[PDB]
Image 1 (cartoon, chains in turn green, orange, purple, blue):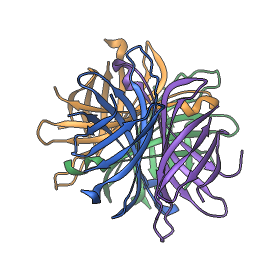
Image 2: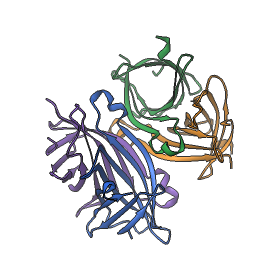
Image 3: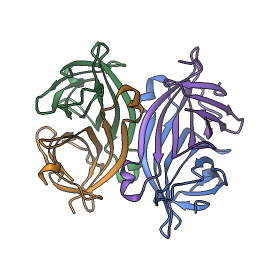
Image 4: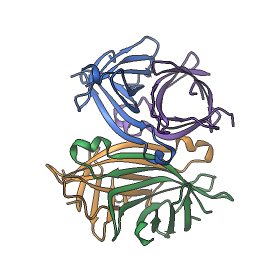
Length: 115
Length: 115
Length: 114
Length: 115
């Protein structure tokens, strides 16, 4: 149930394909200039006791039009049902010098839904 | 630079290839039963001011022999500098029922060297 | 403002007093546990929220989970006042297990109970 | 073993007193202008299994001389011995309008020593 289009609570969209071999591939859209490659992995053989399915993905915010010198990783789980959701925590890291490496990484969370 | 074999503090091993317009491919190891696919992205065109290179990757802990029902993401940066390092922060999510979701994610930090 | 009884999404109760010097004191029920913390007693005019944080160690007369949680976040006043936080829960582990010592999560607190 | 003067890798210094039933009280500094109150809690009855002692504390970055409109919380554990250390992860949150809340919280790690 992961394959498809997902929307977060504030304008972002991603299209993902979940491969048989646990791969996650797609596009993240924040114009073709706000589109980025997404790649990741997911548990292709989860438990059927009501647990969600573990997954993660990465976007590096560089495309042929712009480069924010920053990458985000999302770690979380897919939960199906009538109300399917991907609940995540993410880490945003920017390229800094050594002296500023202390302030390099933001942390947040994101919920994605199919509508 | 990023391409190579890296080791963290505890002793795990990650072999990565940096290619494409920023693809990260490879394996994580902690023997063949401990090997898992890794996938991520990186800033293929970092700043020229001495900043590091942002990157992220994902490992889902399922292979042909084992399934921990969980995935880890590393968010961080590559420093070419003195000895090259990758300094990361990570999130490990496990699939949980919805009632135990509050304790699904661990957070920690990892430094990699080619030594 | 911040002073009052707060509840998170999971029904836990946070009774806190905001002092005039930026101290936060009170009690947390996830019986009760002592909480202490700090807040910005003079935030920005500009519509910014108020930065704050607090800690609870999960030890009282009944039980001891050998753990402490810290919440860091901000208060946003409004028709619906709310406190948006990220938290870190650290348990005592041996050295070899330290890598799995810390959970991370997010709590939203509100003056109305779920 | 917690009561005293602790130092992180970045210069920063913290003086804490551990009260008998779990209180942590002290100052965080790096001159008066750079001095701020800290308060936290610790497990006043740790396990005897050689596990460490859980604690946490908070500093809000406001004193009589300046206001960063920020608060940092440290969550971690005291590890005793000759090489006594406090290992932490932290969250730094800044006040932000609702529009900039995604980028309000920094995450990182710090290690404290008695020397």
